[PDB]
Image: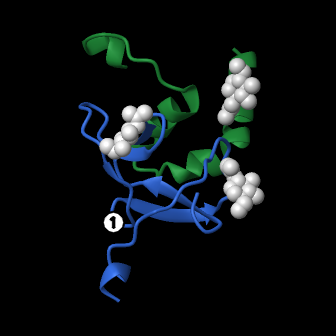
Protein backbone atom coordinates (compact mmCIF):
# COMPACT_ATOMS: atom_id res chain seq x y z
CA UNK A 1 0.00 0.00 0.00
CA UNK A 2 1.17 3.47 -0.86
CA UNK A 3 -0.61 6.82 -0.73
CA UNK A 4 -4.00 5.09 -0.63
CA UNK A 5 -3.26 3.02 -3.76
CA UNK A 6 -2.70 -0.73 -4.20
CA UNK A 7 0.66 -1.63 -5.76
CA UNK A 8 1.24 -5.11 -7.20
CA UNK A 9 4.59 -6.60 -8.38
CA UNK A 10 5.13 -6.86 -12.12
CA UNK A 11 6.95 -10.11 -11.47
CA UNK A 12 8.08 -11.98 -8.38
CA UNK A 13 6.69 -11.60 -4.87
CA UNK A 14 6.92 -9.21 -1.93
CA UNK A 15 8.95 -10.50 0.99
CA UNK A 16 9.97 -9.20 4.40
CA UNK A 17 13.24 -9.93 6.24
CA UNK A 18 11.62 -8.72 9.51
CA UNK A 19 12.23 -4.99 9.11
CA UNK A 20 12.15 -4.13 5.41
CA UNK A 21 10.10 -5.18 2.40
CA UNK A 22 11.67 -6.26 -0.90
CA UNK A 23 10.54 -7.67 -4.23
CA UNK A 24 12.20 -10.83 -5.52
CA UNK A 25 11.83 -13.43 -8.26
CA UNK A 26 10.04 -16.64 -7.26
CA UNK A 27 12.64 -19.27 -8.20
CA UNK A 28 15.72 -17.69 -6.63
CA UNK A 29 16.11 -15.36 -3.67
CA UNK A 30 17.57 -12.08 -4.92
CA UNK A 31 15.86 -9.10 -3.22
CA UNK A 32 15.60 -5.57 -4.60
CA UNK A 33 14.04 -2.31 -3.41
CA UNK A 34 10.36 -1.89 -4.26
CA UNK A 35 10.01 0.91 -6.78
CA UNK A 36 7.53 2.29 -9.29
CA UNK A 37 9.57 0.52 -11.97
CA UNK A 38 8.83 -2.98 -10.66
CA UNK A 39 5.21 -2.55 -9.58
CA UNK A 40 1.93 -1.50 -11.16
CA UNK A 41 -1.10 0.20 -9.68
CA UNK A 42 -4.63 -1.15 -9.79
CA UNK A 43 -7.48 -0.25 -7.44
CA UNK A 44 -7.25 1.40 -4.04
CA UNK A 45 -5.67 0.30 -0.73
CA UNK A 46 -9.07 -0.75 0.66
CA UNK A 47 -10.00 -3.49 -1.82
CA UNK A 48 -7.15 -5.96 -1.27
CA UNK A 49 -7.23 -8.37 1.67
CA UNK A 50 -3.95 -8.75 3.55
CA UNK A 51 -2.49 -5.54 2.11
CA UNK A 52 0.27 -3.88 4.16
CA UNK A 53 1.62 -0.29 4.53
CA UNK A 54 4.96 0.72 2.95
CA UNK A 55 6.65 3.38 0.81
CA UNK A 56 7.34 2.80 -2.87
CA UNK A 57 10.46 4.48 -4.21
CA UNK A 58 10.17 6.95 -7.09
CA UNK A 59 13.51 7.18 -9.00
CA UNK A 60 12.57 10.44 -10.75
CA UNK A 61 11.95 12.64 -7.71
CA UNK A 62 15.61 12.69 -6.38
CA UNK A 63 16.56 14.55 -9.57
CA UNK A 64 13.69 17.09 -9.23
CA UNK B 1 3.32 -27.06 -8.13
CA UNK B 2 6.78 -26.70 -6.63
CA UNK B 3 6.73 -30.03 -4.78
CA UNK B 4 6.45 -31.79 -8.13
CA UNK B 5 9.85 -30.43 -9.18
CA UNK B 6 11.98 -30.30 -6.03
CA UNK B 7 11.33 -29.58 -2.31
CA UNK B 8 7.91 -28.44 -1.12
CA UNK B 9 7.67 -24.68 -0.65
CA UNK B 10 4.88 -23.23 1.48
CA UNK B 11 2.69 -20.52 -0.06
CA UNK B 12 -0.62 -18.77 0.87
CA UNK B 13 -3.42 -20.26 -1.21
CA UNK B 14 -4.65 -16.83 -2.55
CA UNK B 15 -1.13 -16.28 -3.89
CA UNK B 16 -1.10 -19.72 -5.46
CA UNK B 17 -4.22 -18.74 -7.36
CA UNK B 18 -2.66 -15.42 -8.35
CA UNK B 19 0.12 -17.32 -10.11
CA UNK B 20 -2.40 -19.56 -11.83
CA UNK B 21 -4.36 -16.53 -13.06
CA UNK B 22 -1.24 -14.93 -14.53
CA UNK B 23 -0.58 -18.25 -16.26
CA UNK B 24 -3.78 -17.85 -18.30
CA UNK B 25 -3.16 -14.24 -19.29
CA UNK B 26 -5.29 -12.58 -16.60
CA UNK B 27 -3.63 -9.91 -14.47
CA UNK B 28 -3.37 -11.03 -10.84
CA UNK B 29 -5.19 -8.00 -9.47
CA UNK B 30 -8.37 -9.54 -10.86
CA UNK B 31 -8.15 -12.32 -8.29
CA UNK B 32 -7.59 -10.08 -5.31
CA UNK B 33 -10.39 -7.65 -6.16
CA UNK B 34 -12.72 -10.59 -6.77
CA UNK B 35 -11.36 -13.09 -4.23
CA UNK B 36 -14.74 -13.54 -2.55
CA UNK B 37 -16.56 -14.07 -5.85
CA UNK B 38 -13.98 -16.58 -7.00
CA UNK B 39 -14.03 -18.53 -3.75
CA UNK B 40 -17.83 -18.61 -3.85
CA UNK B 41 -17.98 -19.87 -7.44
CA UNK B 42 -15.42 -22.54 -6.55
CA UNK B 43 -17.40 -23.72 -3.53
CA UNK B 44 -20.53 -24.03 -5.65
CA UNK B 45 -18.78 -25.93 -8.45
CA UNK B 46 -17.32 -28.45 -6.01
CA UNK B 47 -20.61 -28.91 -4.16
CA UNK B 48 -22.34 -29.90 -7.41
CA UNK B 49 -19.92 -32.75 -8.16
C1 LIG C 1 16.75 -6.29 6.30
O1 LIG C 1 17.58 -5.77 5.24
C2 LIG C 1 18.08 -4.43 5.52
C3 LIG C 1 18.89 -3.98 4.32
O2 LIG C 1 19.99 -4.85 4.06
C4 LIG C 1 18.93 -4.43 6.81
O3 LIG C 1 19.35 -3.10 7.12
C5 LIG C 1 18.06 -4.95 7.98
O4 LIG C 1 18.84 -5.01 9.18
C6 LIG C 1 17.56 -6.37 7.64
N1 LIG C 1 16.65 -6.83 8.70
C7 LIG C 1 16.86 -7.98 9.34
C8 LIG C 1 15.92 -8.42 10.42
O5 LIG C 1 17.83 -8.69 9.04
C1 LIG D 1 -4.35 -15.55 8.58
O1 LIG D 1 -4.85 -16.65 9.36
C2 LIG D 1 -5.08 -16.32 10.77
C3 LIG D 1 -5.56 -17.58 11.47
O2 LIG D 1 -4.48 -18.48 11.70
C4 LIG D 1 -6.12 -15.18 10.86
O3 LIG D 1 -6.32 -14.81 12.22
C5 LIG D 1 -5.60 -13.96 10.07
O4 LIG D 1 -6.56 -12.90 10.13
C6 LIG D 1 -5.38 -14.37 8.61
N1 LIG D 1 -4.81 -13.24 7.85
C7 LIG D 1 -5.16 -13.01 6.58
C8 LIG D 1 -4.57 -11.85 5.84
O5 LIG D 1 -5.98 -13.75 6.02
C1 LIG E 1 -2.15 2.11 6.65
O1 LIG E 1 -2.06 3.40 7.30
C2 LIG E 1 -3.34 4.10 7.34
C3 LIG E 1 -3.12 5.47 7.94
O2 LIG E 1 -2.46 6.33 7.01
C4 LIG E 1 -4.37 3.26 8.13
O3 LIG E 1 -5.63 3.92 8.16
C5 LIG E 1 -4.53 1.89 7.43
O4 LIG E 1 -5.46 1.08 8.15
C6 LIG E 1 -3.17 1.18 7.39
N1 LIG E 1 -3.30 -0.05 6.60
C7 LIG E 1 -2.62 -1.14 6.92
C8 LIG E 1 -2.78 -2.38 6.09
O5 LIG E 1 -1.86 -1.14 7.89
Residue placed most toward the observer, A35 or B47: A35
Can you tell which quarter of the image residue B10 is in?
top left
Q: Which chain is green?
A: B
Can you tell which quarter of the image residue A6 is in?
bottom right
Say whether residue A11 is left or right of residue A53: left
Residue placed most toward the observer, A33 or B22: A33
Assess disc 1: are there few (<14), some (14-19) or many (≥20) residues with their C-alpha within 10 Å of its C-alpha.
few
Percent across and percent down for residue A44 are: 65, 63
The answer for which chain carries disc 1 is A
Position of A15 relative to A35 (above/below):
above
Specify the quarter for ligand 1.
top left
In the rendered image, the quadrant that contains the C terminus of chain B is: top right
Q: Which chain is blue?
A: A
Q: How many marks?
A: 1
Q: In this figure, which residue is indicated by the disc labeled 1?
A: A37
Residue placed most toward the observer, B11 or A34: A34
Percent across and percent down for residue B20 are: 44, 35
Q: Secondary structure at mark 1?
A: loop
Q: Is residue A2 visible?
A: yes
Say whether residue A10 is left or right of residue B47: left
What residue is drawn where x is 23% and y is 31%?
A28
What residue is drawn where x is 54% and y is 52%?
B29
Position of A59 relative to A28 (above/below):
below
Amino acid sequence: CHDGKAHFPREGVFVSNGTHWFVTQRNFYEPQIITTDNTFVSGNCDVVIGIVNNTVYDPLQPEL
Amino acid sequence: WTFGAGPALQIPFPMQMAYRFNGIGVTQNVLYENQKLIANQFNSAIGKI
